[PDB]
Length: 197
Length: 211
Ligand SMILES: [Fe+3]
Ligand SMILES: [Mg+2]
Ligand SMILES: [Mg+2]
Ligand SMILES: [Mg+2]
Image 1: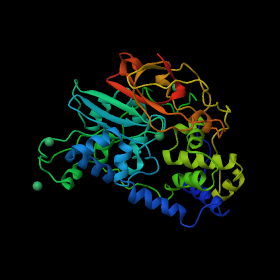
Image 2: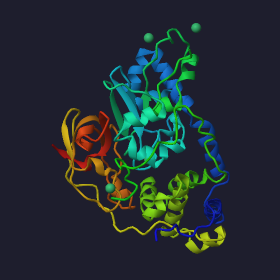
Image 3: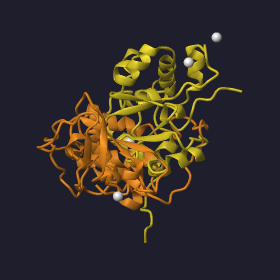
Image 4: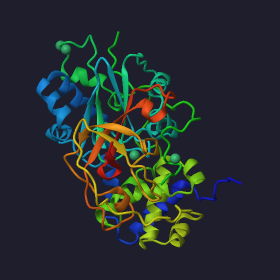
């Protein structure tokens, strides 16, 4: 009762799917290998970090990013699969934004990278919509009682990034220095950019 | 579809397996893990065999206990394989022969889907809307926590997309609709049993009505 079904090892199933399709001429030469390279090397939170650092130092770009995210991202050539309609959401002294896909794993791939295992977890998918303060606290981010937490559930085609607050102690930093402190977790919204002691 | 995949608000789970900025390792943790997404795109872009919406729905169609014990990337292997069989591109026999063992698939659909709604409203930023009190057995991009609930429009998309409840079933009548960022107060969704502020759900026009 309630037992798992019999299954061949997952690697054997996944490669069987590949071989079945490839053996019928349905997969172009180097097709999956090319996607693997795109997923590993091109889709990256370093891109989102570049966008944040630019917004932090360029008031005009910041306004474009917050009103037409797609156009702002396009200037850098960072539009792509699962990242064609972009909305950036602005943290403020009274507002912390957090992103989830409660129904599966929907993520702005090209600018955040493919979602991490934890973002796809049933724990995150179930809990962050209902108790984001506790979830963030458990993850190592304390959000004070007066700051409104706003959770964006990625249920359609909008793909989100968080524009975090620029921390004190970074005045005059170069775009490269600022990029360094904007991590994947800052873009998802579960972390706040950290300045070294 | 009111399936187990509709997890938002479910109680009883433990800690998220992450602390901020912890090592998440490489993009792919096994040599096969790039295959589900790559073969999804082969199916969508090269074969034209199915839509991304159909992939979401076929994963929703995993038997519920099977869904709950299966790692994320494996659910997509199962989903893509199921679609390839359903579309007549592959057989389960050949998959099992190549795999050297059992390759159980998602369950058949129990709904033919539904068309893009005939009567909808163009909403404006600031307007109060209620999520239609409707039950859809096939694919839908409305998590149950917002069904029948009231919120405010924060954004109307400048682009339009096929209605998921139609395209997710490969129907010819998905039309196109914009979506709306609808902001709900946490208390509207979970009463006193929440520690949040607001939740913004990205909802197709056809899921909404004037409040
Ligand atoms: Fe998703
Ligand atoms: Mg300043
Ligand atoms: Mg300097
Ligand atoms: Mg439910």
